[PDB]
Structures are given as C-alpha cells and as structure tokens.
Image (cartoon, rainbow over all chains, first blue to last red; front, top):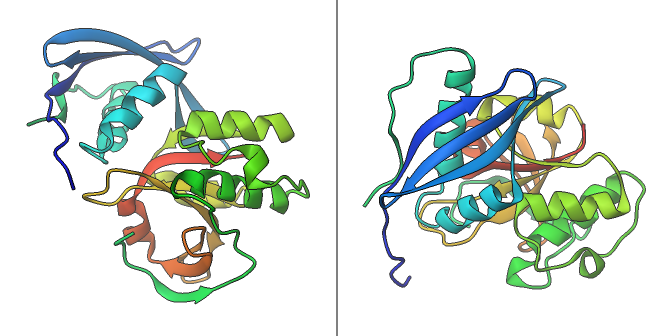
Length: 95
Length: 140
C-alpha cells in the first residue's frame, strides 16, 4: 500500500449525561482540540454508542490508521460510565 | 480479507457486491430480505460505507434500524435480534468490509454471509470479535 500520513490523536475527556445519555468527547488532533458528540444506547442488552454523523465520518477517516479506534473509544467510555477512574489523555492514534 | 474462516462455501443465496464499496448495500439488501422487504443493493446505494449512512438508508425502506459502535461483549445479544451487519476491518486494510452475521451456531461460532465472493463461512467467536471493528447495523 501507499503512505497514509501518520497522526497523534488523543482522547482528552469523556462527559456523560445520565439524563439524556448524551456523551461529549474531546479529542486532540495533533494539538488542535475538537469536541464530538455521541449518545449511549443500551437496547435489549446491546451496549451501543451512536456516534453523531460527523463523529462517524471522523472515525471512518482514521480507521485506516488504527482499525481498533472504536474499541479504544468504547472501552474508555464504558469505564467512565461505570465510574472507574480513567487516566486521560488516552491514545487513539499515535505515530 | 485476510481473516481466518472455516467451512466456506460459495452460496448463491448470498448477495454478491457489485463494486468494491458495494458490500454495505449488499448486506443491506440481505438484511431487508430477512424481514420480507425486497430492495436491490443498487437502490440502497453501493457507495454507502459508514454505519450511519447505511442505517439511515435502511430506515428509508423499513423502520427501527440502528447504526452504532457496539461492544465485543454484545455479540450474542446482537444475534438474538436476527441478522445484523458487521464491519470487518483487518490489520493493514485501508477499508472496512461489511458482512452479514446470520447467527451463531450451537458451538458458538459466528455464521457469516460475505458479499465479497457471495460465500457462507464460519468464524470462531474470538476471531470474529478481533476483526469486527464494532461498527454494526442492527434492528432491535
């Protein structure tokens, strides 16, 4: 394959709203901060995260660099929701 | 497509994708077919690759489809709803590949209908969980 330019993308924070189930994610994209939203969805014991349309587009663009990136984001999210202490920042993509 | 499978057979009941990106729409056609809705992959749109865009399109012909990143641990709860679509993304690939998860057999293996060649095969639950990137289209 060709060269895909590498990046450092970190997850800086996860803010979960117990009432609305909304989730605010703050990423660092090579130092530039950006906020994306999602909604937590537990239905018939299926533990899902409904990314916003723009978050899904963003994740799809970096999947070629790290196909595990939703597993990382999801793992952190469920730990946060369950009240575990999570040390941030958490690497999503590194060079 | 380098992931490990067994008992693979060509199966003309699996809908074969018509283009590289067509696997989402091919899965979408089979997902709707299982619910007595008959829409060709061309009408669904063989450019659709993201779970958001695929669930949104299925909800033009049906109702109640979700397109979410799902935990590995929800595999059996997903298959309890019927067939669902899983985005496979193996190491080194620059693209995802949608497959239809038909169910799980009695030994717990995952039964896959794959539109790449139009085949049916099995995967161990552990291997399936590693290659599936969590992105999923399903109808609770």
